[PDB]
Image (tube, coloured by chain):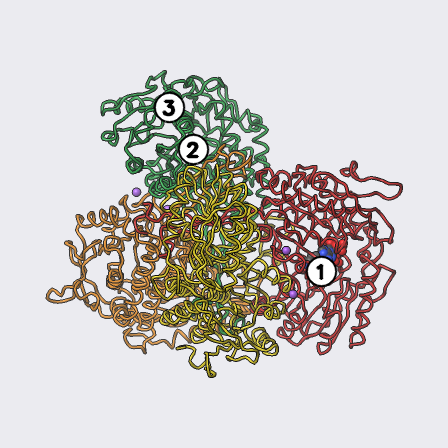
Chain colours: A yellow, B red, C orange, D green
């Protein structure tokens, strides 16, 4: 709508969103329904591209898009991104409504994602802190004497941005931004679950001046996207999604540069000297935000004996006072999960915990096909490691609570999951904090706050099953750029006099 | 021998080299013959590890090796590497003899590789220019106000170093060095073709103090190594080899950090204003060194009309005056190719060129199962692109010569191969040079010199089919290390007064 | 005017500009006339502050201004600068008119300075590439084992910005920008000759939100400014002016951080392979722009035998076709010099050159008290070094032309002046260029272009008599900021296990 | 002796040390006695250079020394420094004996300084982390479009190293090392009080290969050194000494690059949660080491109410159990002060404190012309600020103890002195620590340890009266090096296609 007026076609029924084929919106492949977790109803359809159009798009992106993007000076590229931000911002409510509707995201969380996407675009100027190579004089070795080196980065070419359902707007804007600010062409592939926000952003970008042959948005479901990843014209693949899909992506792609943000949940550690008010408050929010559908959501809480009681009590109270329902009501604190399937898994995981010695301390009641209460399950340390909620990531509002004797047990348990994205530690003692910071095997540690990736003001990414490489203002240059080395030989030419 | 006295076991016949299993030398798997390209004779045997020993080694490297390496302070780790250099250096001739014998490398080139390996170890102190994270103050965004960030690198854990046959000693030492200087454990997997130099270096390292449970040397042939790459305890894979094997490696490994140095040959461009003496001299050497068995070997020469004649003439003269035979004779300029198979391919490729309009300008005569003359094949521009010598990398001393009308044709042809490792340009005009530097799609460009990776004083790596990521003093930190972000939240705590 | 309506007071006669005293505009000291080089007429008066007000201002800047500036978050500080840019830009013509009138600057050059000042403000976001300290792990020495370091920069406090007459608007905005973007308070002290543009910018900044107690503009003539430089509350002094005044400034200030941009002219070298059209064009402009009143103005031209003739001829033609007069006429190419005194010196210097063997090739005729023709004086190498035009900087449109036999003589002569700000070299041979780049003792070298500092997109500053330290986007952080080191001791505390 | 055999001349009596005149040892100026604080006896004489020899030395350093140093490749320069370290190390005892004798330094502290000097030389390889400029692409502004920049550092030329009496060997080696590793020539000017260690180091360097015309050691007393500082051939001045002398140095030198390490003492803050054992132990040592003759010595202790008692008690006990006397006895903990004059001042300062309400808690008794007891003087907060021991730096083993109500009072008092070199904070709460780190106006803060500059593994330097700029591995490059900018103009030349 609004910016998509000429694009969207209302074929008797729901609005139909076509793919962008690096030049023109279209698509001749199967049409696919897009539903809302609020009521399982169809709110639109997206046109997927035919194999022939995928092939043609890639050919355009490669043969022409790489140069449109690279040959547009940086000052112009940034102008494009700044303009795109302006457009998205004046269409805020429209962007947010689609998020609430398509993603089942509470109105406040939906507004937050639009603002993040706007800010990310505007702050592309900070990504520039990573522009500018290195000079390497040669007189520090006899073999390189009277030699000189210059190392600078160049865009790889065509970057494939694969996006998850839980941040349908931000992830797309984020990847497009860091790929473009450095001069790359981009193939965006959003979750078929909620691909509407991505189409809206791509249009805003095109309206803002983004080289028409340098970007693409293909509505391809799951494995049909493999055609893109495996293509040799795709020099990089920026993927945010599940460990399991990420694995398949690399196996299909083969040699290329990758950024793999594979989530998993995060553990939170509470030391005896922690401000329990802050802790309880932050931990509770970390558990339920967006119905736990945040890769940086808290899935396990670990607290030392002397504060475990209060802490768990306060968090349980907090989770209990939450209001569930339709996200539209700014009254509601928690909306629905992306699918009934996801709730099924959460219920099963809660049963498993109880059978293995676990006790629910708050929530636990399913309220509908896609509605559930944010849950907090207590578990004894000697039994938690075998619980599904521990061993795996149950993408839902549910966390385990475990009493520990000391920091070492806290750390050990925190590290015992197969993931290593972020971790949180509340407490005040520098030494204990330092210890934790060194031994927690995660990409990021939040001291006295819940894990919050934000727009990547601070880089993030995983360790272990949570992936490889980071995303962040500036740091993302490593995934979409390659080094170029220039060596000059002046031996005997008289520049230097033996040196 | 010497440092391998207690290790090597002479079971009636040839010396038998066991694998190092992160603690003790051994192996209960098939024994494999190691032959010399000088006379196809068996010079030794290596003991491959059983699946059970591979499993056990990885378990040691992971559970214990990661910590031995990480918990050894850096000052101590560097001492180890410096010591290892001392040991290899006093055993120079021994190391070189094995290179000449096992790799068919001319005595001078063999001495050069030992010296490179010694220097690489000693210069691990320069890799330290990449130690030391980033501080990120939070007041440049309202959402991060009263927040702070610290980003530092940590070793990934266990790094798998897969090595090629043409630099059997250097590549191994190089990878072990940058992996260890940053605190990682390493599984070295040398080419089964010439795994002896690697065993010698590993022993020197162990003798020097390298944590015994933090390193491994497994004599596994080709695909049996996949067991290592695919294992989850292997967090990184540093691979130097062929495009085709590299592809398989990533597909087997899945998500992990990779450095893929996939070679291919390099093109050399000669402008009308180039010093043709230097050019001819450097280009000829770039063509024949180590019998063209250098990933950075020149495979194509492009020269502007007015100098093509002289240039090709001078290079042909030079290639013609070379002496072939056994590498032992410091008289010989060119030894044998690693296998008769490699020569077969070179002969076939030369035929193909001639059939497609090509004419030999020097060499072309096979001198034995593993001996051939360094060849220079002339080809008209309108026909070279379909020639096997162009489309592929014929790992042998053979290059195509092509006359071009101008720099644009030179660049176009240079970029027309599927590889993009390095490229060379001889000439003096800044503008033409700048143009070439911008448009040549390669990891590195050598101005007025032949492509020479050396010890990585200047980083190198490929573009296109030549791979992803770089190796170099300092730059290699990106492949064996991961970022750790620490975010501190001081909101309302009184550190800052609104700012 | 416009933004200065409430500020400027028209006391029967000319407009009277008061000083800004870190809180309120005012001043109780002598009033001073401000004249225009276009007609020696008084166009305004500035109120200088009393010793008591200087003292009070410094006390405010120190006790309160340092914190207003430091405690304003960066995101807010940048907003202030961006806003200030908007204000100056909408008042462009007003800013430019005052420049043309007060500085005698040609309308186009005046518009250029306003745009530079606007751009400099807007690009303060690029100065941020220099925000963010260093982490220093301690295990690379035994004595620092189990220790850790963090190094970050902090604003020094109160920065004194002393400004020259030739870039009355830019220099002021530039210094205020880099001092403020990092959190410092600023005392601006413009040339009493043309202090009006500075007052206009300061007002725009105050209007934009600049903490009122964190900035000051004092109309103090020459030596009366010493009171500021010598004060201990002034932690830094950013000075752009003459070598001789800079010398006095440091001697008065004593220990503090300084940036000393002391100008002098620049030499231009033309090699035999240079595009003489470009060369002649750029060199001529470098000679006459703003009537040679540019610190980066060309004062000496050196060309190799074979091109000297044409080059000097083309430049002479060009200088000859220039139109002199009042700057207002967009027809005029050259306006007046800041004072008749400056012309006196130029005429004397031209006489000296001729007496010492020099011959005028273009210009030489004085056209009025403050008007002169852009001059080009030929001089034989064996006699040029004793000429006033060589030994000194004659701030006027005049340069020496000298034929040389080769690059070495060119370089030698270029380096023979007491200054070392910038230098220019036209030619195409990489080796000769490299040679020149290494041996020219200057802060900056321009290849195939005239020296052009611009807004400091590329850092600049001098060597020898041209000063110390640089100014530039990002690089200026060194002059207004100080390092803070934080060392943490964890010995025996259990963070590390021997390492 | 030993390495000074041919140099030192025993003219009937004490050994006579000549100055090194950039080529040959000598000197025709007044001879000066060098005495030992252990017994006020003359242990040697140094030959000062005549004005004519100073002039000649500078001329050599400038005309020839700059190039010997710059034209010696870095790999060779480092070899020189590594060799010099070897020589000093094998002559350890000799170096230490002279320190104990000439500086009155306890044998252990003397051995420590020799080891520091050895390590500093060997670690010059870590200074290399600061070698290698910046590439600046031009397409981020329209005015710099099709332009490019390269910024690299060059040695300034001739660096003057002025050294203090308390670290007669280290400071000299330190300054020579960072000046030389980057390619500068050096004029060393040691304290006339104890210039012997410097002569020994210079000889070791000359023996190690240091270009003979690139270094100088001039035995000039106080103000006679001004001749050096004021000379235009001296491009940099690295000075470690008193605030007052530093001030004079800059006023004499004028415009040049300076590093001013002006000391003053340091304050130590003890929070209620601090390990009082560690605190007391570190604080006591910080008070008495080298008889308080350390610029980083503790002069003021501030502890929160609840721990003040114990803390002061434990420190008093510790200071009391110290043994004073001749430094030779490894039994002695404290040797003499450099002169009786220094003790006079300490006694006067202790009287002043008592008169103003202060009470001695330990020590206070003078034991001889140059011997005193390490003292701890208690003072009430409401009266300490007017005490001489607070307002000034009494270079002796004496500190004030002051009870405070909270961190804010601690910080306020800590910041109340005119100095700002380092500061120490003992405690464990992150927030309180963070607060202190932000508000303490010093160049460096030591958390849970006494201020210890060491060899500059972590950079240090002052704020306020303690100076400007830092010294440290790597960081010192800023004081002895200058930037060189190279801008390339390719406008319309066809490198870029509009970008
Ligand atoms: N890019 C660079 O910087 C660079 C540098 C040097 C060389 N190279 C290139 O690399 C090649 C080196 O020669 P090469 O003939 O030895 O090539 P290669 O066969 O590709 O070398 C492969 C290395 O990988 C191992 N390997 C083979 N199959 C494997 C599998 N399925 N799984 C895991 N590991 C496997 C090999 O062991 P086995 O010996 O047991 O098969 C060998 O150690 C050349 O093409 C050269 O151009 C590139
Ligand atoms: Na692939
Ligand atoms: Na895998
Ligand atoms: Na002063
Ligand atoms: Na001076």
In contact (CB < 8 Å): disc 2 and disc 1 = no
> Residue D315: which disc?
3
Residue most toward the right? B12
* Residue at mark 3 to residue at mark 1: CA–CA distance: 68 Å
Q: Identify which residue, D249 or A161, lies in the foreground.
A: A161
Q: Is residue A244 positioned above or below D408 on the image?
A: below
Q: Is residue C496 visible?
A: yes
The chain under label 1 reads: B
User: Is ligand 1 less than 8 Å from the beta carbon at label 1?
Assistant: yes
Q: Quadrant of ligand 1?
A: bottom right
Q: Is residue B193 positioned above or below B16 on the image?
A: below
* Residue at mark 2 to residue at mark 3: CA–CA distance: 14 Å
Q: Nearer the viewer, mark 2 or mark 1?
A: 1
In contact (CB < 8 Å): disc 3 and disc 1 = no
Residue most toward the left? C12
Left or right: A67 with respect to C170? right
Report whether mark 3 lies on the same chain as mark 1.
no
Q: Identify which residue, A372 or C33, lies in the foreground.
A: A372
Q: Residue at x 33, y 30 (%)?
A: D301
Of mark 2 and mark 3, the one earlier in the sequence is 3
Q: Around disc 1, counting alpha carbons within 10 Å, would you say few (fewer than 14), some (14 to 19), or many (20 or more)?
A: some
> Residue D449: which disc?
2
Which residue is the site of mark 1?
B245
Report whether mark 2 lies on the same chain as mark 3.
yes
Whole-percent x and y of residue B446? 63, 61
């Amino acid at each position: 709508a609004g910016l998509l007026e000429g694009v969207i076609k209302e074929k008797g029924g729901v609005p139909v969103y076509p793919s962008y084929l690096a030049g023109e919106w279209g698509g001749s492949g199967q049409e696919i329904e897009v539903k809302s977790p609020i009521d399982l109803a169809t709110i639109a359809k997206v046109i997927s591209p035919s194999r022939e159009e995928v092939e043609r798009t890639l050919d355009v992106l490669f043969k022409r898009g790489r140069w449109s993007a690279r040959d547009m000076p940086g000052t112009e590229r940034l102008a494009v991104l700044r303009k795109a931000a302006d457009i998205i911002e004046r269409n805020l409510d429209v962007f947010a409504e689609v998020l609430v509707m398509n993603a089942g995201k509470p109105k406040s969380a939906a507004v937050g994602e639009v603002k993040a996407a706007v800010d990310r675009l505007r702050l592309a100027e900070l990504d520039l802190k990573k522009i500018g190579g290195d000079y390497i004089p040669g007189d520090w070795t006899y073999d390189t004497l009277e030699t000189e080196g210059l190392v600078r980065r160049e865009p790889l070419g065509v970057v494939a941005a694969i996006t998850p359902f839980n941040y349908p707007l931000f992830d797309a804007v984020n990847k497009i931004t860091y790929s473009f600010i450095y001069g790359n062409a981009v193939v965006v592939k959003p979750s078929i679950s909620d691909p509407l926000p991505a189409a809206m952003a791509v249009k805003a970008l095109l309206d803002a001046g983004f080289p028409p042959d340098a970007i693409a948005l293909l509505n391809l479901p799951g494995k049909e996207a493999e055609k893109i990843v495996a293509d040799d014209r795709v020099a990089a693949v920026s993927f945010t999604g599940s460990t399991e899909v990420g694995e398949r992506v690399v196996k299909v792609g083969g040699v290329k540069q990758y950024v793999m943000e594979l989530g998993g949940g995060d553990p939170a550690i509470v030391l005896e000297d922690a401000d329990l008010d802050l802790a309880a408050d932050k931990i509770a929010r970390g558990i339920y935000s967006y119905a736990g559908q945040r890769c940086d959501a808290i899935k396990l809480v670990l607290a030392e004996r002397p504060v475990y009681g209060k802490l768990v009590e306060e968090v349980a109270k907090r989770l209990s006072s939450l209001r569930v329902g339709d996200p539209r009501d700014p009254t509601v604190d928690v909306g629905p999960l992306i699918s009934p399937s996801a709730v099924d898994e959460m219920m099963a995981a809660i049963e498993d915990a109880v059978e293995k010695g676990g006790r629910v301390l708050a929530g636990g009641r399913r309220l509908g096909p896609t509605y559930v209460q944010p849950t907090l399950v207590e578990a004894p340390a000697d039994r938690v490691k075998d619980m599904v909620l521990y061993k795996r990531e149950v993408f839902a509002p549910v966390a385990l609570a475990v009493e520990v004797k000391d920091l070492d047990q806290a750390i050990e348990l925190a590290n015992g999951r197969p993931y290593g994205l972020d971790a949180a530690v509340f407490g005040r003692d520098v030494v204990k904090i330092r210890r934790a910071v060194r031994l927690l095997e995660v990409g990021a540690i939040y001291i006295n706050d819940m894990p919050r990736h934000g727009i990547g003001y601070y880089p993030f990414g995983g360790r272990k099953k949570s992936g490889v490489f980071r995303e962040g203002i500036g740091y993302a240059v490593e995934a979409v750029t390659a080094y170029k080395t220039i060596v000059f030989n002046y031996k005997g030419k008289g520049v230097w006099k033996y040196e």
